Amino acid sequence: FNAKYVAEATGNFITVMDALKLNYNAKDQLHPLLAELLISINRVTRDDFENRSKLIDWIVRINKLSIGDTLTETQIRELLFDLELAYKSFYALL
Image (cartoon, rainbow, N blue to C red; front, side, top):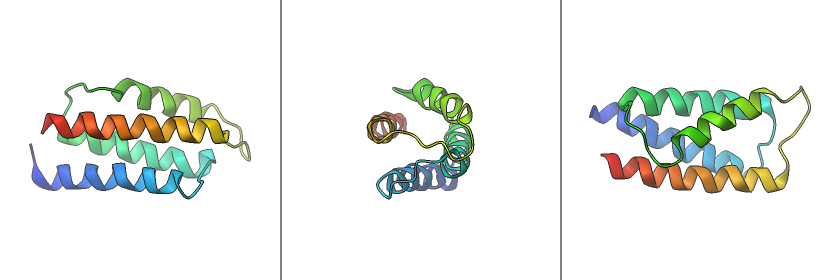
C-alpha cells in the first residue's frame, strides 16, 4: 500500500464524518465529498471491505436528489454509522 494514498483516504473518511456531524445534508455538499472519498479509497486498493458497496449505494441515492432537497436526519445518522463501519473495515485491510 502507498503511504500517502492511505493518509489521504484516512483524511477523507474523517472529513465526511466531520461534515455529517456539522449537518451537511445537501447533494451539493455530500456528492463531491463522497466521490473524493471513494476515489481515494480505491486509489489505495481495489480490495473489498465491509460497507464498501453501501457507500457506493449512497452515491447513487445522493445523486438521485434534486437541488435543495436534503437527506433526512435519520439518513444522515445512517450514513455516519455506515462510514464508521467502513473506515474500521478499511483500516483492517492495511
